[PDB]
Image (cartoon, helix red, strand yellow):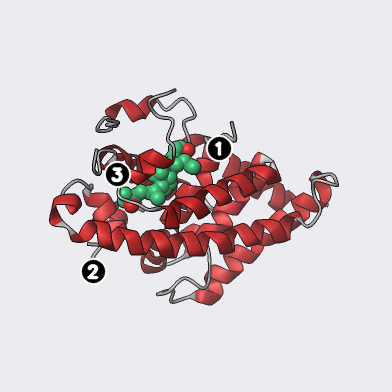
């Protein structure tokens, strides 16, 4: 009941994700090292992690079917507003409900200049998302749907974005119906869209604490140019 | 603002 186009879309997103997510963490070595001893001691490392992750999210976004049809401006607006959300999403793959250096916990994030106001709901998110035990097919569709959202502020051709997203949305809904067996499939789509809603709230809180954090020039100094451009300066 | 780096990475 999955059309050939929908199977095409899944194959494309799977490969796109495989080409942008290295589970071996080979590149983490090139980041400024994590410091655990420590005010904002993890900021340099996590900033590089996030900067790296933005690059990977962009590479993924470009391979989303239809994304190349949007204008340069709309591509920018979608990536700027969704970046942190897709990084939180993709990070679920490394999250465990149970390396050692690149295994991050609450205190690490706290040492990057954030409070429990963000960290608590972020952990709730990760646990709740993990619980869904999504197929990888569903995981990559959710990231793409997150990126191509009509309602992002600054979108010009919202009708086009929405049309590109509906195609991705219909592919997910059909995949679940045809490929994800119950009970695991029970209301799975609704629960995935709720995760996207959770992500909007996580996005807003991160934005707040990022403004506070990056207000001090001595902390802004510890960020990267890409982070400053995408998250703001 | 302008986003040269983001612009460049999006091709
Ligand atoms: C509970 C999930 C793991 C937590 C881990 C550490 C804290 C991070 C960087 C979160 C912070 C709120 C972001 C700090 C960014 C800053 C610019 C300092 O505000 C975002 C995603 C989180 C994280 C992401 C992890 C990864 C590892 C791996 O899954 C690849 C991903 O692209 C990035």
State yes or no: Cβ of the residue under disc 3 lies below 8 Å from any atom of ligand 1.
yes
Q: Which mark is residue B4?
A: none
Give the chain of mark 1: A
Residue A168 appears anywhere in the view: no
Give the CA separation, mark 3 to mark 2: 21 Å
Q: Quadrant of residue A81?
A: bottom left
Can you give x and y, in whole percent of width and height, for residue A221 in the image?
15, 49
Q: Is A184 situated left or right of A193 in this image?
A: right
Q: Residue furthest right?
A: A182
User: Which corner quadrant of the image does residue A229 belong to?
Assistant: bottom left
Mark 1 nearby-residue class (10 Å; few <14, some 14–19, many ≥20): some
Q: Which residue is mark 1?
A: A93
Q: CA distance from mark 2 to mark 1?
A: 33 Å
Q: Residues within 10 Å of mark 3 (few under 14, many from 20)?
A: some
Q: How far from the left and from the top, in percent, is residue A63?
A: 50, 49
Q: Which mark is residue B1?
A: 2
CA distance separating discs 1 and 3: 19 Å
Q: Earlier in the sequence, mark 1 or mark 3?
A: 3
Mark 3 highlights which residue? A47
């Amino acid at each position: 009941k999955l059309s050939e186009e929908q199977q095409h879309i899944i194959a494309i997103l799977l490969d796109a994700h495989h080409k942008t997510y290295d589970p071996t963490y080979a590149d983490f070595r090139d980041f400024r090292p994590p410091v655990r001893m420590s005010p904002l001691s993890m900021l340099p490392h996590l900033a590089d992690l996030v900067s790296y992750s933005i690059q990977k999210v962009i590479g993924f976004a470009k391979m989303i079917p239809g994304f190349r049809d949007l204008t340069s401006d709309d591509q920018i607006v979608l990536l700027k507003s969704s970046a942190i959300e897709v990084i939180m999403l993709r990070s679920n793959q490394s999250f465990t409900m149970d390396s050692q250096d690149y295994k991050y916990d609450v205190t690490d994030v706290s040492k990057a200049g954030h409070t429990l106001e963000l960290i608590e709901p972020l952990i709730k998110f990760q646990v709740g998302l993990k619980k869904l035990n999504l197929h990888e097919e569903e995981h990559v569709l959710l990231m793409a749907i997150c990126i191509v959202s009509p309602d992002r502020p600054g979108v010009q051709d919202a009708k086009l974005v929405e049309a590109i997203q509906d195609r991705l949305s219909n592919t997910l809904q059909t995949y679940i119906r045809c490929r994800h067996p119950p009970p695991g499939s029970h209301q799975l789509y609704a629960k995935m869209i709720q995760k996207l809603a959770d992500l909007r709230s996580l996005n807003e809180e991160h934005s707040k604490q990022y403004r506070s954090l990056s207000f001090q020039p001595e902390n802004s100094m510890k960020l990267t140019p890409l982070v400053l451009e995408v998250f703001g300066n | 603002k302008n986003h040269p780096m983001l612009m460049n990475l999006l091709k």
